[PDB]
Length: 180
Length: 180
Length: 51
Image 1 (cartoon, rainbow over the protein chains, first blue to last red):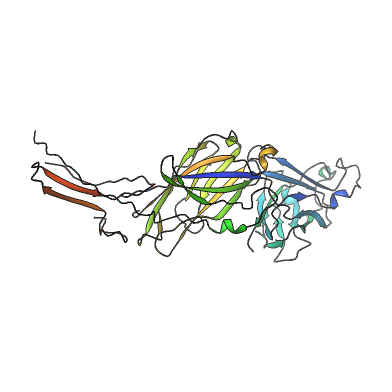
Image 2 (tube, rainbow over the protein chains, first blue to last red; image 1 turned 90 degrees about the horizontal axis):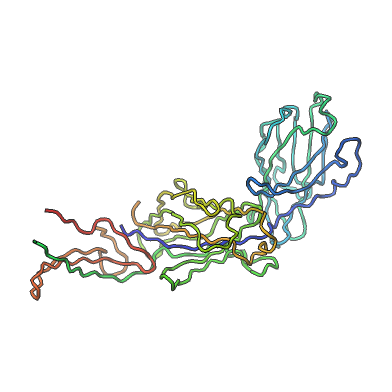
């Protein structure tokens, strides 16, 4: 009954995403004990073959029974879209499983350079107690820097304190936006 | 035997398509890097002479290694019909071959303002995995918006990462009607 | 029975009528179907034929 179509062509274009990640400054602590890793903060990105996400892994060292605060880990800012870009962090949840995840008692990722609405995502062991943060405005050239906060329960077994072993793996998604 | 004909007299004067295609606010970014194009979304409706269709060329610049979605892409928005329009979405497949189509891991199309039953047709590279959606009401005054969701695998060569080259071309057939 | 039309003059979109033409003596039946440019047109119920 008067069924009508349009037959629309769609074309797509590919370019480097405008967010990009810099390793910050705390990747040059260059001081470490016999820990295999010669640094304290690692920043690198590899192409996931399953889904093609620009995965950016980070290695953070936490001190058992003693809270640790970071002030310069990652900075986010537009490098090609020269507009006012809005960013926000959303927590996803634990990925993988090492059965050590009950031994972490608090873990937070937050902005340091721009101060805004709550500006922290908190993980209580395996569950997520803070869903997402608010937006933040970023201009051309200036970047929002991201801190960290790790606290590991001191009851961790001695055999896993040498630093080789991984005790957690958290996914957080930071979402760019053109609106507040 | 007992065969009397019809001799139909069959009146046609086609009216303008009451839906019509509006660029939306995505073309109002008006800002871009030194990538050649001043705009990211090139929405334009062109008279196709090859087969006689009001084909609309719109550009959806999908960023490499990062799933990108758009909110205000296309407006199916009745200005010449005084009733309520009921539409559903069916996709065709591929047009031509850029030899880069395998680099797409997902291409699904979901609206923002109109909300209904699944409301997304999803491509899987060259193949198709979603058939169609349900009906949605579009009447006078209330105006329907079309969205998108594009993800590109970051294994694309840097030469095609400039945004000039077209990486894929798909057909979508939206069927607007006056009845559900 | 579409019974709906924009500012196109005809208050309907499908017409069915028949007149007895004297030139050929045929029960010529008149059907009118509105078209749309750049747009395939399909229908469901135009005419019913049965004894």
